[PDB]
Each structure stands twice: as structure tokens, then as C-alpha cells.
Image (cartoon, rainbow, N blue to C red; front, side, top):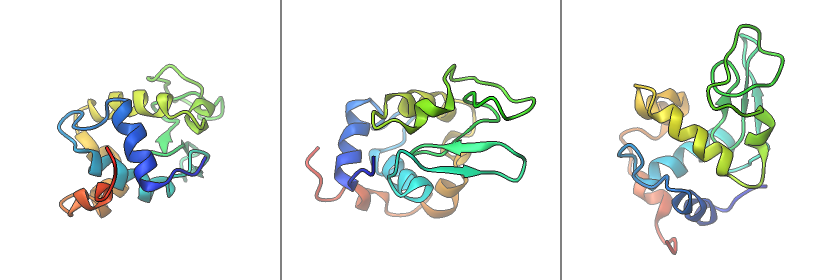
Amino acid sequence: KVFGRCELAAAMKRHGLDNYRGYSLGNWVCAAKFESNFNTQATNRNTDGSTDYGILQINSRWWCNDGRTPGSRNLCNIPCSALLSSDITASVNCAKKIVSDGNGMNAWVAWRNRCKGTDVQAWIRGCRL
């Protein structure tokens, strides 16, 4: 599923991501924009052999099981395929674990490089929320 901007903002809010660990909704929408362009089915293979999955491009090295990432963990206790669903519940629950891990949203390199410090409220501007 390719979400609309405000559509995703609303789904993220419904799933309790707004201000989670102090990160406003716009931060989450911004991260999703640059990680996946709002596409739940996004995947990307990393040089180390791991793969990133879903709207927030969660990586198989630590967070989900895809059966093809040697030496990895599955800390969210989910198949990586669950991160591709039109239903964002799995991605949101896993993102909550990730953002609690110690480095906040810096875990998402694209958030650090493209969202951090910017006017992220613009990502939810206009939205009915």
C-alpha cells in the first residue's frame, strides 16, 4: 500500500506513534517519506546482506526474521514480511522498540540526514488529525 501523507499521519497517530519517545508525528512522517516514499512494500538490500523492510525500512540484522541474514537477531519477534503489510501495526510496534534502543530516531540514518533539525511539522500541515 502506498499511503497518502495525511493518511499515514493519521494511521501513525492511531497506533500511538505521535510524540512516542518525544518524537512528534512529523518526525515519523518525514522518516517514512525518505525511507519508503510511504510504500509499505518497500524493500532494500544492504551491502552486508541484510534487508530493510516496509514504511520505516526496518532491518533484518536486528529486528525481524527473513531467514537469509546470517548471525542476525529478530528482536521484534516477527517475520520481516509482516513489515510489508497494508496494516502498519507490525511496523509501528517494531519502530517503538527501535526508537527505545538508545539512540532515538538516529537509528534511521535517513531521519538523521534529512529530517533531524528541520521543520518536520510541515509533514502534518493541513492534515485532519
